[PDB]
Image: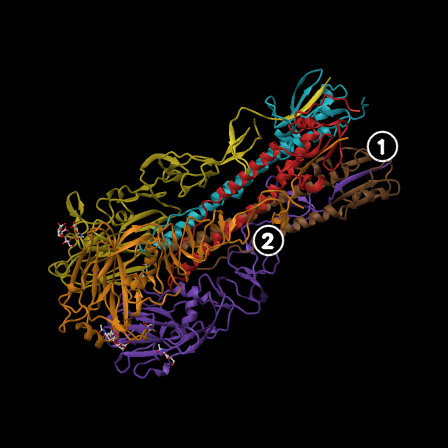
Chain colours: A yellow, B purple, C orange, D brown, E red, F cyan
Amino acid sequence: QDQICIGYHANNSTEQVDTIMEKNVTVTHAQDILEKTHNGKLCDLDGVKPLILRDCSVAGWLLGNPMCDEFINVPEWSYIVEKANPTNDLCYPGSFNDYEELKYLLSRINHFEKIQIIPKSSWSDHEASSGVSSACPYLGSPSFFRNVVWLIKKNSAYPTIKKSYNNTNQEDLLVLWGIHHPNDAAEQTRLYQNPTTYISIGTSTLNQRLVPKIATRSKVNGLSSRMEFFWTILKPNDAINFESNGNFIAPEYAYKIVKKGDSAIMKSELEYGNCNTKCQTPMGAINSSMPFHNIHPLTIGECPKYVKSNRLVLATGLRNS
Amino acid sequence: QDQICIGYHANNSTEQVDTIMEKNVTVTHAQDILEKTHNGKLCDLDGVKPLILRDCSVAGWLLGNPMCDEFINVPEWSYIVEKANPTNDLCYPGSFNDYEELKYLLSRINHFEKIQIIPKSSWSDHEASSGVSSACPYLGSPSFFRNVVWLIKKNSAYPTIKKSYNNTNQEDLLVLWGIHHPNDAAEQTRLYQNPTTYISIGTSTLNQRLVPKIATRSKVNGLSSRMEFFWTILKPNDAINFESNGNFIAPEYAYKIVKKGDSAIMKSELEYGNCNTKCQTPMGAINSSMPFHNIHPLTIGECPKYVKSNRLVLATGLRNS
Amino acid sequence: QDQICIGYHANNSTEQVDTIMEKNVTVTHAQDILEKTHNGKLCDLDGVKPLILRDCSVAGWLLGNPMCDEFINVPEWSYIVEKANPTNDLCYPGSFNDYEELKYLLSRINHFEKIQIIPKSSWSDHEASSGVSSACPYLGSPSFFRNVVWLIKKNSAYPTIKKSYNNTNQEDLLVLWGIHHPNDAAEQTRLYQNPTTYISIGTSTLNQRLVPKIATRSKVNGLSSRMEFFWTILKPNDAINFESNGNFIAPEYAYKIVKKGDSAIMKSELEYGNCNTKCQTPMGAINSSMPFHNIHPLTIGECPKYVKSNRLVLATGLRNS
Amino acid sequence: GLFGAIAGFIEGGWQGMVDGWYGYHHSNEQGSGYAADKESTQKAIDGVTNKVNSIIDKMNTQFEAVGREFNNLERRIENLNKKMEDGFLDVWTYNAELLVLMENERTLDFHDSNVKNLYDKVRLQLRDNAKELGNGCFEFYHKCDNECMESIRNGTYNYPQYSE
Amino acid sequence: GLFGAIAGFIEGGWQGMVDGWYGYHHSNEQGSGYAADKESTQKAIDGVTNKVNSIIDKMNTQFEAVGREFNNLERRIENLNKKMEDGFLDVWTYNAELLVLMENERTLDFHDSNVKNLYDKVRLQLRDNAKELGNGCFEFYHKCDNECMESIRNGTYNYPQYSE
Amino acid sequence: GLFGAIAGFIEGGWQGMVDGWYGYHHSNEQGSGYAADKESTQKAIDGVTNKVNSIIDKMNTQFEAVGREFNNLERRIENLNKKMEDGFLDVWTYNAELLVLMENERTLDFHDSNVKNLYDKVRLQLRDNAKELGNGCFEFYHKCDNECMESIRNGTYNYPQYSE
Ligand SMILES: CC(=O)N[C@H]1[C@H]([C@H](O)[C@H](O)CO)O[C@@](O[C@@H]2[C@@H](O)[C@H](O)O[C@H](CO)[C@@H]2O)(C(=O)O)C[C@@H]1O
Ligand SMILES: CC(=O)N[C@H]1[C@H]([C@H](O)[C@H](O)CO)O[C@@](O[C@@H]2[C@@H](O)[C@H](O)O[C@H](CO)[C@@H]2O)(C(=O)O)C[C@@H]1O
Ligand SMILES: CC(=O)N[C@H]1[C@H]([C@H](O)[C@H](O)CO)O[C@@](O[C@@H]2[C@@H](O)[C@H](O)O[C@H](CO)[C@@H]2O)(C(=O)O)C[C@@H]1O
Ligand SMILES: *[C@@H]1O[C@H](CO)[C@@H](O)[C@H](O)[C@H]1NC(C)=O
Ligand SMILES: *[C@@H]1O[C@H](CO)[C@@H](O)[C@H](O)[C@H]1NC(C)=O
Ligand SMILES: *[C@@H]1O[C@H](CO)[C@@H](O)[C@H](O)[C@H]1NC(C)=O
């Protein structure tokens, strides 16, 4: 005689998944949709290679820390890597105005082209080669930032400067300058003769006037003196005008912005891996087709979607026993 | 003999809907819950009509751009429309302090009543009718903002001003003033005699002292001079005190705020439609009972809930074949 | 003959719950997961008791409002309670710089230890006991803030002060000071002889220079004069340097921060209950095992998760009739 | 058919039935025709109407988006602003789309359920006195007149009858 | 009844049954009474207990709301602050309410399922030796003693028996 | 088994079946063996494939997290920033986990459904000409050759046959 039966698949897979009502339920086929693996390396993002400041901050890079010459001229970059606590920041103590806002601009640029907008030679009536500290040493000898220039008196005289400058390029200039805040009145005359000074700076948009604050402060890097830096963006066809009678750390090199685009500033301790990816996190890169990952929320490139879980498995088959 | 059967509806509707497991599944009855249609017009919101600055910004309106007389006196409004890039902003170049914060206040007001708080006549010892530029032309002739007044020297003399002013209304005053920043020392004496000036301003809360920044700047609208505007809110029963010896663009008209309420500042290129709605977006108005819409996130009035989808259909009936 | 039946539970419970398709559906067993009950009291959070300023703000506390002596010395606290509108704030009219940021720091501290860093005695060449107002009355007699000290001229003379101060503790100091803004030039000489003054203040990080704004202002608390307060955080082993020739409200007591940790500033009208909890909201405390509550979003301690619903019941049993 | 009734064992749907969602077609000696079950059809109306208004009610305070403007040195909070408003608009857009897809399926299966439960209401009456055809129909071991059926639909059906 | 068992073909519930969710009532010669199926009732306990603790676990890091205060010229970020904290509190409040409504339905249907599957466990034993009444009961073509039933409940039931 | 088929009345699964999700084992005179139903197995493939790609599509614009840095006197907006980015990352992490748990259950019940509906497709053909064993099998009141079965699987099965 004959019977006939109806039944389903079972097999040799050990792979549990979860439902709303029961956990660790073994099934036949199961798909994993969470990627949990990186390569622990900092890669190029599609062939264009990152800017990895090493022990430099953005400030030391942009201003020209003489410990930062690796980055005197930096090619087009895909994203930037800064350490948590870069050792080479402001070697002469002070501050950098609107610093996080400028770091925010940087997350939207892929290429600067440094250009010299006022030659160190062009300074006829002031000294422009004696503006150097021990707090900014270059190879043991007293140096200073390369991109700005610390002008001082010549022949016991700081005649008032009027330097204008017209951006005739097709690109915005990032332009940096600063003021020097002396430690005392004696220092102020030793350096600039005139006891009472200022720096005015104007564009179409910027209208500032800076006076230095002479004052006793704690020592940092050996000094009680401070340097305070300011920056602006020069629009194509606009001029920047500087007039000052002392304490003026004049620009010398500025940056053309020749590639805005999508970038990021990554805080990471890692260093250049020598690879290529389409998706980068600060603890390594990801090569995965998975729609999700749980590595790290800050990410750049064509990326799986970050998620906090350590386990996402989707059931395809049926119950197995 | 007899049978009897059990069965369900089918009909002549072509209307597919989606499930988690299958797409484009045809059904009998289906309800649409997404509204995708506007009238492309800017309407009154329940009978009270919008303020549409045309080529004016809030700054030109509030300060009195002489290209902005359409809005010399503006009735109660329901919401405001500004273009992306209004042509009539600050005709004399400069800035307007805490501007986005004042635009934020405006999103909470429906009615100003302009009132004259210091007559142009009241200025005995200064000239108050020669304070006009070509950068603010009214009908070809050199004009200037109407709501503030650009005082200058008289008989080669700017005696120091002390004007006090006590808000004795039941409403907060919006009060605007400014400082003029000259291009050079020559200009400063030509205009106000005294080489060194200031404007102090105090209320219960505000304690400022302004000094003008003389400086060379690029030309905007023909000028290297700048005008910088400041504003405050005068509390009912408080006074505002002004003391200055030059560079003082004094107020003349202020605004009583006589209807705070729910409003918005809409950026839109559109112009007055001549209709009425209960819900407005910047690309047109909506008349719909639908609980959702996908038109535009910024919305004012009794509004369906914005959603990014282009298709939401809810199944009512059953499968059809 | 015999039958046998199959059936389910019904009972005498009246407890409806809701589904996606039907409301108020009666069932057998039902679990409630929303907690809707507080004790209307302000409790200790696990045995450590709150700081309840009563009619004091943080500013009156920290600066030493002479109406605020309850809090001259405040023990370790678990969280702070401020009223919506504390009556004892700045008794001499003025402002307190970066005030919300300092309130934000406070939400991360559980204990200050007030220490005297410059004795009122230490002032040899200025008067330090005549700096008192009627706007800050203590028991009817003209007083002033306790933690700062309003120095004035002595023997018709305010010689320029240079006071340095080195934080040699293991903890950050919160250090407060201020400037006095006079009502007129007459007042300025009556108080400090020298017509033109300043206060410079420097640490490793702070480099400021303050000049007082002489100006006519409306009366507050009887005065047109203003006091403006500033604060800083002194790092262990750093110094703060003060140099001034008038208008300087010098510090006398500072705060060591000896317990950072998790805290909160609660706005509440309530007063000390005398109890203990593990979870506190500003309208009372919660003792509940429930995973949810709908009392108030701002919460401190081991807390159920806030939710806006007034009803969450989960079905355990089955349908009942 | 998750419940296997609709488009499962019954083939198509009854174009002819214009009175409710579900019902009957009978093939007897006084006449032929269609009727719809008030009990079940009405219960389903109450079903989806409640579904709709609970979906609408569940999302009636959602997220409004106010306009804030930022200046040129406020690109960080301007971005923060943008990505928070965007971000909310995205999770609410997801929620609506997701909730809809789910409730659509659970609704189709709901109607299917109602059918199979109707088929069971009848089957659990005509036990012996009819045979299950296989396509949702019962052939009668007796004669069933219009009035016999009215007893059926309203489910009070007289079983006190022989068989062969 | 989505599965048509509970309040579907069985009418009410058994007030008398005080031992589990589901079970039996028997009407035989040595006695009468109620029993509950450990197998199914226990499986359901495990069910909803797991449901509860997964709902609680799914929302145990949620969104805390810290207090930030803003001054008078910071109305824009103060609003931003407010509407972001509000906005989160709203999506989390939705999620809780939504998740609850869904799991409530899927739970009621779960119990229903358990019933119809019990009814099928018995029916798939007594094939010939009983008749389906229609209201969830089986009438016996033999005599069924207390001990016959213990064989039933634990589902090892001896079919080696005649019929007529 | 919510539908009571899988691990319900059928005991285990068929290790031997390596051709589809569901199917048959036959025990006749020309041979024995296994076959799988293209109709149902293929329909299920289409099912979960659609489920997967709709889950992936439903979360393909989600929430990106840009880096903003704040200075020392910006601890309030820095916190605001942090707790908004965190907060989103948390609701999206919930949504993914929740959606997965739900769709897993509704999927297991989907396969179960497919089984019980296959069992019903056969049962609704062999009405008289076989008996329901109880463990998902039909014993034949006739002889059923390989070719009889091919008529079965493709469901065109010839009923014009006696019984006893
Ligand atoms: C531009 C210049 O004068 N350079 C000086 C420098 C400056 O005068 C000073 O930093 C004021 O800005 O002073 C230098 O020398 C000394 C250092 O060798 C040492 O670290 O600290 C000393 C006392 O504080 C003193 O400043 C310097 O900083 O390099 C010498 C340099 O030529
Ligand atoms: C109040 C006053 O003096 N008005 C002048 C104006 C001002 O003196 C000047 O703008 C300083 O604020 O100067 C005016 O005239 C010229 C313009 O006709 C032209 O666009 O630019 C010239 C050189 O830069 C010059 O300023 C003006 O702006 O209208 C004449 C007006 O009476
Ligand atoms: C430190 C000192 O001089 N204290 C004075 C005080 C100050 O001179 C003044 O507040 C300037 O900062 O003036 C005092 O007296 C008067 C008050 O009694 C009254 O409320 O208002 C008066 C006019 O405006 C006047 O100021 C004071 O405020 O206590 C007297 C005190 O010794
Ligand atoms: C800079 O140079 C351009 C081109 O030579 C000129 O037209 C322009 O007016 C100048 N810009 C300024 C602001 O001086
Ligand atoms: C303004 O006027 C009112 C009413 O006349 C008066 O009481 C008040 O003190 C004045 N306000 C100020 C601040 O001068
Ligand atoms: C403060 O005192 C310490 C310990 O005596 C000393 O080493 C340090 O340099 C001083 N700090 C400053 C900034 O003066």
Residue at image mark 1: D163
Residue C183's x, y, as percent? Answer: 26, 74
Q: B315 or A97: which is nearer to us? A: B315
Furthest residue in direction front, as rendered: E30
Image quadrant where residue A197 sits: bottom left
Q: Position of residue E1 (x, y in %)?
A: 67, 42
Instruction: Report crowding for label 1: few under 14, some 14 to 19, many 20 or more residues within 10 A (C-alpha).
Output: few
Is the residue indicated by label 2 positioned so its CB lies within 8 Å of ligand 5?
Answer: no
Q: Secondary structure at mark 1?
A: loop
Rendered view: A204 above or below F43: below
Real-space CA distance between mark 2 and mark 1, rounded to the nearest whole angstrom: 54 Å
Q: Where is ligand 5, by quadrant?
A: bottom left
Residue B40 lies left or right of residue C69; in this view the side is: right
Asked whether residue A11 is in view, the answer is: yes
Kindly identify which residue carries mark 2.
D56
Q: Nearer the viewer, residue F74 or A212?
A: F74
Q: Chain of mark 1?
A: D
Relative to F113, residue C61 above or below: below
Total tally of numbered discs in the picture: 2
Q: Which quadrant of the rendered structure holds the N terminus of chain A?
A: top right
Q: Residue furthest left?
A: A155
B165 horizontally vs B1: left or right: left
* Residue C320: x %, y % from top left: 65, 45
Residue type, numbered disc 1: Ser
